[PDB]
Image 1 (cartoon, helix red, strand yellow):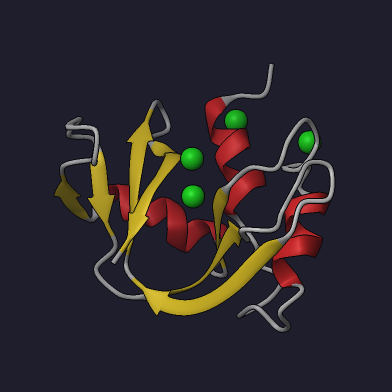
Image 2 (tube, helix red, strand yellow):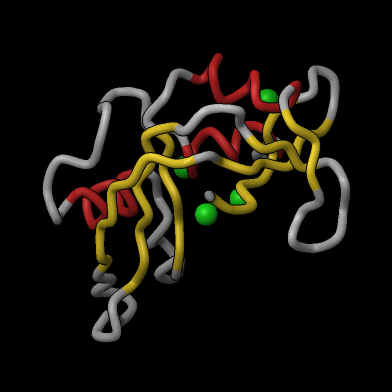
Length: 124
Ligand SMILES: [Cl-]
Ligand SMILES: [Cl-]
Ligand SMILES: [Cl-]
Ligand SMILES: [Cl-]
Protein backbone atom coordinates (compact mmCIF):
# COMPACT_ATOMS: atom_id res chain seq x y z
CA UNK A 1 0.00 0.00 0.00
CA UNK A 2 2.82 2.55 0.59
CA UNK A 3 4.34 3.43 -2.84
CA UNK A 4 8.09 2.81 -3.37
CA UNK A 5 8.78 6.53 -3.54
CA UNK A 6 6.82 7.35 -0.38
CA UNK A 7 8.61 4.58 1.55
CA UNK A 8 12.01 6.03 0.53
CA UNK A 9 10.96 9.49 1.78
CA UNK A 10 9.67 8.10 5.06
CA UNK A 11 12.76 5.96 5.72
CA UNK A 12 15.50 8.30 4.51
CA UNK A 13 14.51 11.97 4.41
CA UNK A 14 15.15 14.33 7.32
CA UNK A 15 15.31 17.82 5.85
CA UNK A 16 14.23 19.43 9.12
CA UNK A 17 17.73 19.19 10.61
CA UNK A 18 21.07 19.89 8.92
CA UNK A 19 22.85 17.20 10.92
CA UNK A 20 22.39 14.68 13.73
CA UNK A 21 22.37 16.69 16.93
CA UNK A 22 22.84 14.17 19.76
CA UNK A 23 23.76 10.52 20.23
CA UNK A 24 20.04 9.95 20.68
CA UNK A 25 19.04 11.14 17.21
CA UNK A 26 18.81 7.61 15.81
CA UNK A 27 16.70 6.18 18.65
CA UNK A 28 14.22 9.04 18.28
CA UNK A 29 14.02 9.00 14.47
CA UNK A 30 13.92 5.24 13.99
CA UNK A 31 10.94 5.20 16.34
CA UNK A 32 9.05 8.17 14.99
CA UNK A 33 9.44 7.09 11.33
CA UNK A 34 7.97 3.76 12.41
CA UNK A 35 11.04 1.68 11.71
CA UNK A 36 11.08 -0.17 15.06
CA UNK A 37 7.43 -1.23 14.74
CA UNK A 38 7.51 -4.97 14.06
CA UNK A 39 11.21 -5.26 14.66
CA UNK A 40 14.35 -3.19 14.90
CA UNK A 41 15.46 -2.28 11.36
CA UNK A 42 19.21 -3.03 11.69
CA UNK A 43 20.62 -0.27 9.51
CA UNK A 44 19.09 2.95 8.18
CA UNK A 45 20.47 6.19 6.71
CA UNK A 46 18.82 9.61 6.98
CA UNK A 47 19.70 12.40 4.48
CA UNK A 48 19.64 16.01 5.73
CA UNK A 49 19.14 17.77 2.38
CA UNK A 50 16.05 19.04 0.68
CA UNK A 51 13.88 16.50 -1.10
CA UNK A 52 14.50 18.36 -4.37
CA UNK A 53 18.30 17.91 -4.01
CA UNK A 54 17.95 14.18 -3.30
CA UNK A 55 15.56 13.69 -6.24
CA UNK A 56 18.11 15.49 -8.49
CA UNK A 57 20.64 12.66 -7.86
CA UNK A 58 18.59 10.54 -10.30
CA UNK A 59 20.03 12.71 -13.10
CA UNK A 60 23.62 12.62 -11.82
CA UNK A 61 26.35 9.94 -12.12
CA UNK A 62 25.00 6.58 -13.31
CA UNK A 63 26.72 3.71 -11.47
CA UNK A 64 26.06 0.04 -10.69
CA UNK A 65 24.06 -0.87 -7.57
CA UNK A 66 25.59 -3.36 -5.13
CA UNK A 67 23.12 -5.89 -6.48
CA UNK A 68 24.35 -5.52 -10.06
CA UNK A 69 21.38 -3.48 -11.33
CA UNK A 70 22.29 -0.35 -13.28
CA UNK A 71 19.68 2.22 -12.18
CA UNK A 72 21.90 3.57 -9.38
CA UNK A 73 23.15 7.20 -9.30
CA UNK A 74 25.92 8.76 -7.21
CA UNK A 75 25.54 12.39 -6.13
CA UNK A 76 28.20 14.71 -7.56
CA UNK A 77 28.67 16.49 -4.25
CA UNK A 78 28.72 15.27 -0.67
CA UNK A 79 25.56 15.56 1.45
CA UNK A 80 24.87 15.64 5.20
CA UNK A 81 23.75 12.17 6.32
CA UNK A 82 23.25 10.17 9.55
CA UNK A 83 23.97 6.44 9.68
CA UNK A 84 21.78 4.59 12.27
CA UNK A 85 22.92 1.07 13.22
CA UNK A 86 21.69 -1.22 15.98
CA UNK A 87 24.22 -1.77 18.76
CA UNK A 88 25.32 -5.22 19.87
CA UNK A 89 22.94 -4.76 22.83
CA UNK A 90 19.74 -3.84 20.95
CA UNK A 91 16.73 -6.13 21.30
CA UNK A 92 13.20 -5.86 19.99
CA UNK A 93 11.35 -4.18 21.36
CA UNK A 94 14.04 -2.18 23.09
CA UNK A 95 15.81 -1.12 19.91
CA UNK A 96 19.08 0.77 20.51
CA UNK A 97 21.02 2.54 17.77
CA UNK A 98 24.45 4.10 17.34
CA UNK A 99 24.32 7.52 15.58
CA UNK A 100 27.07 8.43 13.13
CA UNK A 101 26.91 11.81 11.39
CA UNK A 102 28.97 12.28 8.22
CA UNK A 103 29.22 14.22 4.99
CA UNK A 104 29.40 12.05 1.91
CA UNK A 105 28.13 11.16 -1.53
CA UNK A 106 24.94 9.09 -1.64
CA UNK A 107 24.08 6.33 -4.12
CA UNK A 108 20.39 5.71 -4.79
CA UNK A 109 18.36 3.47 -7.13
CA UNK A 110 15.77 5.37 -9.17
CA UNK A 111 12.60 4.34 -10.95
CA UNK A 112 9.31 5.40 -12.43
CA UNK A 113 7.71 8.49 -13.86
CA UNK A 114 8.65 10.67 -12.38
CA UNK A 115 12.04 9.02 -11.95
CA UNK A 116 12.74 9.36 -8.27
CA UNK A 117 14.74 7.63 -5.55
CA UNK A 118 13.25 4.32 -4.43
CA UNK A 119 16.16 2.67 -2.60
CA UNK A 120 19.20 3.84 -0.65
CA UNK A 121 22.20 1.79 -1.83
CA UNK A 122 25.20 3.22 0.01
CA UNK A 123 27.23 6.28 0.82
CA UNK A 124 30.85 7.04 -0.15
CL1 LIG B 1 4.44 8.56 -4.35
CL1 LIG C 1 4.28 5.04 8.78
CL1 LIG D 1 19.96 2.55 4.51
CL1 LIG E 1 15.97 1.59 0.95
